Amino acid sequence: GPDQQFFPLATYRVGAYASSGVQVWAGMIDYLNYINQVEGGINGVKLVWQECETEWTAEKGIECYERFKNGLDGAPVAVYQPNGAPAAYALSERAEVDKIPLITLGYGRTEATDGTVFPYNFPVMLTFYSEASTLVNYIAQREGGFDRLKGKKIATLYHDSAYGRETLGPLKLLAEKYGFENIQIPVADPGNEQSAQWRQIRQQNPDWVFLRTWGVSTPVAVKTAARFGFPVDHIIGDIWASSSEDVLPAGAAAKGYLALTPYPAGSDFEIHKRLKQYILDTGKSDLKDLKNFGSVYYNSGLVNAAVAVEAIRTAQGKFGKRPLNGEEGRWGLEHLNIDDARLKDMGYLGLMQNLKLSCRDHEGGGAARVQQWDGANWTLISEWIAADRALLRPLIDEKAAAFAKEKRLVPRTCN
């Protein structure tokens, strides 16, 4: 058991979000199962995992972290994924003290992109800052070039929360550069009522709506848009508004709806067929219902698990075929270099983007794909759209420095 590498799993199987959550965990588990049985673990090192119920709350999330941070029956922790924004936010400072890398895929502190200020916090693959850039870059691709953005209107309809306000900075910057009208429209919690917002949108008739709602406000946004006659295929959802469950309640009013994703739905990727061949057909897999096997939730589990696995694998290249430290796990993360060649090997070519992290860059990705909803299924309608991360970097540097000043931290020198 100490000979194995511990993979802590902070999961929720109770409450309103259990239905979606179980699809995510099943993705992580099946991929972990696959690595053990088909590749004999990671370079010979077997993987052991255990679940702790977090009930989607920060209070229990924190208790799970404290239960796991020391390992399981000897097996140490290399990386930790709280799977929860409130838990992740609360854990950041004590994770640094314990030298345990926090991974938040597509969420978390955007300023933690700067690993000189956030040594053990990794908002991997896509931050909301980068998402803004990719959103704009896709618009530009659709309008015929960045020149065409001048004279365009882009409205952002956002849940009034830290999550919704995150894109205020980058969208303002991008609007100054490319000259599109930057319309920012808040939606108060819970967001059951949106008539004023969509009345405004019909009046202003923007060319695109960047939909950054969450939970209940997302199907309502779509339903209301159709009511006010705004064309739904001019609406592009946040990655956290890109699920079937986000749009199914809206019924046929959601036909044509666009959404961004770092892990597109689909059960026809290379890795997915290996899963069917090995754990699905053999009835080994955690998923109760096979009907969600390419669901976006399931695929986030696959990508979430693969990132950690590659990080571990990367670090073994300097620490040998053995269970790893969080301090070593941090080294692996910061040296992640996922190629297209590498993606082809593990079969994540269409599913996961390239990753190149550094001490300076704990994001390492910044791309997304666009998929379209027809009322029943998603359809990929774009390649990977890369963000202009160089353009946004001063905002990140500024934000991380303010934090380092406030918390009185000495930034790591990676020069």
Image (cartoon, helix red, strand yellow):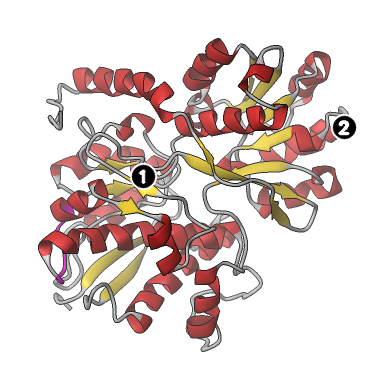
Please state, as top left, top right, bottom left or bottom right, where the N terminus lies in the image.
bottom left
Reply yes or no: does residue 204 show up in magenta: no
Q: Nearer the viewer, residue 401 or 197?
A: 401
Magenta part of the chain:
321-326
Q: Residue at x 22, y 42 (%)?
A: 120
**Coordinates of residue 77 in the picture (x, y in percent):** 21, 61
The answer to whether residue 399 is above or below residue 338 is above
Kindly identify the amino acid type of the residue bearing the numbered disc 2: Arg
- Mark 2, secondary structure of its residue: helix
Magenta stretch secondary structure, dominant? loop
Left or right: residue 187 compared with residue 298: right
Question: Mark 1 = which residue?
Answer: 87
Reply yes or no: does residue 323 show up in magenta: yes
Q: Residue at x 59, y 27 (%)?
A: 136
Q: Bin the neighbour count of mark 1 within 10 Å (Cα to Cα): few under 14, some 14-19, many 20 and up.
A: many
Left or right: residue 175 compared with residue 378: left
* Contact check, label 2 and label 1, Cβ < 8 Å: no
- Mark 1, secondary structure of its residue: helix
Residue 266 sits in quarter: bottom right
Task: Count numbered badges in the picture.
Answer: 2
Q: Nearer the viewer, residue 404 or 141?
A: 141
Q: Bin the neighbour count of mark 2 within 10 Å (Cα to Cα): few under 14, some 14-19, many 20 and up.
A: few
Kindly identify the amino acid type of the residue bearing the numbered disc 1: Ala
Q: Residue at x 71, y 54 (%)?
A: 379
Indicate which label's residue lies in the foreground, 2 or 1. Answer: 2
**Coordinates of residue 348 in the picture (x, y in percent):** 47, 62
Question: Mark 2 = which residue?
Answer: 227
Please state, as top left, top right, bottom left or bottom right, where the C terminus lies in the image.
top left
> Is residue 14 visible to the viewer in this orientation of the structure?
no
